[PDB]
Image (cartoon, rainbow over all chains, first blue to last red; front, side, top):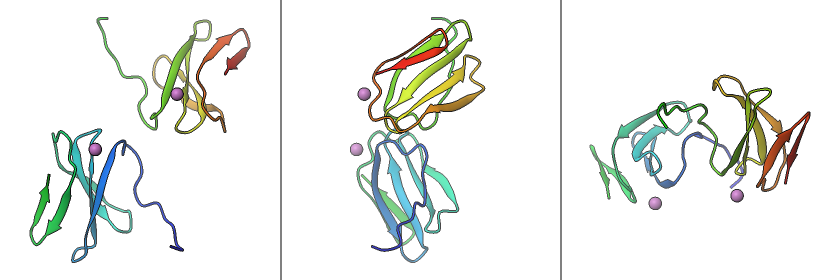
Length: 70
Length: 70
Ligand code: NI
Ligand code: NI
């Protein structure tokens, strides 16, 4: 709990759970206000919208080649 | 109600009432999530932060050379 850091900020109103892909060092999360699932590097450099036109994403998890979401 | 337009969007979360200075043609509004009062031209071009470190702005009005906020 020492080195606090802000990785991503902006249009993240109504954020949902955050998921880490350890094998790829990639963060995945869902934004309900825009209805998208975004991903980005752990260093806070890259960010892109991965899935569009969702209603209310609640859960998401990365395993092998796939992202599962509820 | 004909020509709908978006002037400003960004770090507005807990947006409060808007107000207009007709003589100078600049909009004023307050953002509670950041505790600021901002200005902007009706053209939607110039935007800046006018007051800092507010707690929960509720009302504001511009008359003459002064701006009143509660
Ligand atoms: Ni939710
Ligand atoms: Ni309020």
